[PDB]
Amino acid sequence: MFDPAEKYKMDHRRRGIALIFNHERFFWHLTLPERRGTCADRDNLTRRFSDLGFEVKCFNDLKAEELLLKIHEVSTVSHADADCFVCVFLSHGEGNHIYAYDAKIEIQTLTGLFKGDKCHSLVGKPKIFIIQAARGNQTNITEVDAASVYTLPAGADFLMCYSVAEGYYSHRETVNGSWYIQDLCEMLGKYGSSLEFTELLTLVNRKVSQRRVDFCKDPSAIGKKQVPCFASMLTKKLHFFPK
Amino acid sequence: FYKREMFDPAEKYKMDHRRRGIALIFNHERFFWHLTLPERRGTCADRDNLTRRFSDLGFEVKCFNDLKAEELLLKIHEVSTVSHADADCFVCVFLSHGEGNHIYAYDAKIEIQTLTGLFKGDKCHSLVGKPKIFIIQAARGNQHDVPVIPDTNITEVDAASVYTLPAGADFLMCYSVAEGYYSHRETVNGSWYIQDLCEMLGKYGSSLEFTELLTLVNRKVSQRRVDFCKDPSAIGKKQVPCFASMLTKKLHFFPKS
C-alpha cells in the first residue's frame, strides 16, 4: 500500500560512513589560492556527523589518484549493515570538476562509484554529497568566491547539496570557516537528530541567504549575496533519529 | 507563542493572500519543420491534467499552445511585470522538448535563465520572498525525421538533455528527468512525470509540504517499468526525476479561507 509519508529504513547496525575530503593548499602549477578556514569546517563537520552516529573519516590534501583510490575503496566495501552514506568535499571547483591537490576530478565519476550497479549494498539507501567548492580567486577575513560548480543531481536516492548557486557567491571566514558549512553544522547540531533532512537543508538555505552583504569589511564584497541549493533525487523521507 | 520572534525551524511561507497566484502552462506539441523535432503526442493530456490540479489548488491557470519564441517571451514578460502583491506564489510549467540550458518554443529555443531571470528580485518585487515554482517536462526529441517540411497508446522514450539547474532564492525548479536517465510519455495517457505529479497533487497536494510531495513523485516515477511484452527497446531506460530547491521555508497549499 502506497504510503505518502514513507521513510528510509534507518534501522541498521551502523549509521554509516561519512567521508570528508579537505583541501587547504594546491600544487603551485594549478595557481590556486589557499583556503584558510577550511580546517574549522572539517572539525565542525566531524563533530556534527559523529554526533549523528556516522563513522567519520577525513583526508587532507590528497592527490587526485590517492583520492580516487580511497573513494573507490570505500565504494567496494559492504554497506549492508549501514543506513546511508555521506561524502563531503571541501575545495575549489569548476563546472563539473572539483580540485584535488594536483588536478581536478569529475564529480560524476565520484558519484557514479555509488550508483546501484557499482555498489549493491547502498541500493535504496540515501547517498548524500555535500559540496563546498567555488572559483578560487587568482585575524578573521571573509573571502568571497564566485559560484563555478554546476549544481547537478546524481541518480536515484542521491542528495546533492551545494554551498552556492550560479550567479551567487560563496563566503569563507579565515577563522570561523565557510558561511555554508557553519550554518549547516549549526542546524545539524540543533535539529539534525529530529528534523527531516531536506527540511533542515531548507533552513540552511534561509540562514545563508539572510547573511547580510550590505556592509563589508572589504568594500569589494558588498552586495555579493550567497544562496545555497540542493538537488534531490531521494524517494523517501530522511531522518537521523538517535539509534 | 503569545507572539512570535526568532529563528523557527518550522517556518512556512505565508499563504494568506487574497489569491493563490497565477499558473502559466506553456504547451508544445508541434515544431517548425526546420528544427527537425518530432511531435509530442500526449502533451495535451498533460496540459489538461495540470490545469485541473492547479485550479483545484486555487491557482488562476493560463495555458498557451505552440507559441513562437517571441510570443512566449512577450507573454511571460507581461506576467512578470504586473503586480503579484495579492498573490501567494507563482507557478510556471513548460511542456516541450529541450537541450542543455534551452527549452524549445515553436520556432526556436529559449534559455531557461532568461525565463527565470524575469522574476528575480526587484525585476519582480511583488514576488520577492514568495515561492516561484518552475516545472519542466522537456528532454531530447528523437530526431529520426526528415529536414523537409511535411490512435493507440504508445510509450515514447527520450534521453535527458536539459540541465537540472536552480534559479535564485525562493525558486523551486522541478525536472521530469535527470542526466543519465530517460523521460517517458504515453501518446494517450501523457507523461509519466506529469501523470504521477497530478495524481499526487490530487491526493496530497492540499495538505503535504510541496517538496515532500515532489519526493513522492520521485519514488512513483522511479518505480515505473515499461511493459516488456509490448515494446521493448525500453528495457532499462529508467526514469528518475529531480528538483533543485532554493526555497527558504516550508511550502503548503492548504485550502484558502
Image (cartoon, coloured by chain):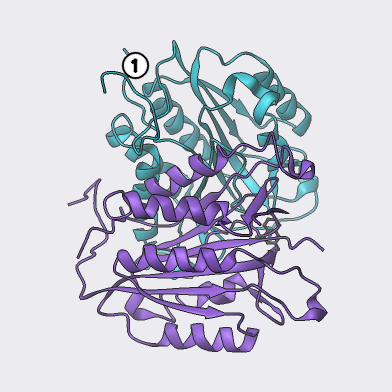
Chain colours: A purple, B cyan
Where is residue A228? Give x, y as percent.
56, 48
A36 with respect to B188 (left or right): right
Q: Nearer the viewer, residue A19 or A183?
A: A183
Q: Residue furthest front?
A: A139
Q: Secondary structure at mark 1?
A: loop
- B176 to the left or right of A78: right
Along the line of sight, the residue nearer the viewer: A168 or B178: A168
The residue under label 1 is which amino acid type? Lys
Residue A100 located left or right of residue A159: right
Q: What residue does disc 1 label?
A: B256
Nearest to the observer: residue B174 or residue A50: A50
Instruction: Indicate the chain on which mark 1 is placed.
Output: B
The structure residue drawn at horizontal position 40% and vertical position 26%, both measured from the top left corner, is B52
The reply to whether residue B68 is in sight is: yes
Does A205 appear above or below A99?
A: above
Q: Is B52 located above or below residue A157 in the figure?
A: above
Q: Residue at x 79, y 76 (%)?
A: A30
